[PDB]
Structure formats: structure tokens, C-alpha cells
Image (cartoon, rainbow, N blue to C red; front, side, top):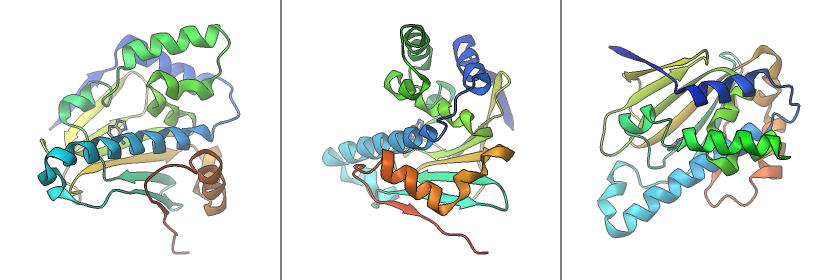
Length: 210
Ligand SMILES: Nc1ncnc2[nH]cnc12
């Protein structure tokens, strides 16, 4: 069964802004998603310090980037703490209602969209480049779920039947037709080196068969 939910009004407004504003520096989406993955890896590492069985679901802590030119998707995979169903419904573990309010006030007081991550809602920068986003996630305390939204006011949550993950989060970006530069190896390397050089977990960029 699929459950369909309405976004809180502030999040729907944030997403409409991101989608319709003219803003050329779109590459920041990848820095923000990597930063979210890094934070999730830090959390499971911290919990494992006093309970090593938390890593029974996978001891490797890393971030993978998987482009797929056939599907026009870019997938960011981490082995971090993951999300329970309640985390997914509550704006993917963020304080997005309050963070959106602070961000929009900041945009009036001389901030630009690249500061989105300072307000805790960096995930939504994915919609600079994606028409649809799928999040697959597995937390130690819950089942594997899939979240999906094409914006437009609603999101869905279902139990995921795909390949098991062990623990972590996969963010699947269904890219807009004019944003395929983010599938190119050389463009992804440029972004990671510019914005994410000092992330403290290994980032592997997968290659494609062609
Ligand atoms: N990668 C991620 N891990 C856990 N919670 C998240 N919320 C948004 N992205 C996340």
C-alpha cells in the first residue's frame, strides 16, 4: 500500500520557489546532499561508540555517487543512520518548517539560494536539477521505505520491496532534460573537488558501461 501525504504549506512554498526561481549556480545541490550524507554517517558513528551492535547492519561508512545516463538519474548512496518512517514524514529528519521561515527571511536580508544548507533544508536544493526525487532508506529500528515526490504539493511513502540496503539512504535524482551535465564524470569530479574536498568519508564515483 502507498500512503499519500500533503506537504506542510511552508515546504510547498519553499519547493515552488526553488523550482521557479532563475538561479544559474545549480551545482550546489550536490554539495548539500553530500553534506547531509556526511551528517548521517557521523550520527551512526557516534551511536556506535557506546553500542557497537549498531554497526551489525554494515560496518563500512562511505558515500557512493552513481550516474546512469540511460535512466537519466544520479544516485547518492550513504551507509549512514537512515530514516524511520516518522523521520520521512517529518520532512526527512529536518526542522523544515522553522528552517524554511528563517531561510526566506534571509533571502530578503541579502542572502542567496546557495546558503540554503545553513537553514537545515539543503535537501530541497535537489529540485534545482530534478523533476522527481526518490529516497530509499533503512534505519536499524524500522523497515525499508521509499519516499517520492515530483513536487506539486504531495509526497508518497511505501514499504520498499527492492534490493535490501542493510542501513542507510539512497537519494535518486530524476534529472530534468536540460540538466544532464550532472551525469558527466568530469563535471561531477569538478563539483566534488570544489565543494566537498574535506568530507571525512570516502566518496566513490561509479563509472558507466557504454
Ligand atoms: N542522507 C540522509 N540521511 C539521513 N537523513 C536524511 N535526511 C535527508 N537526507 C538524509
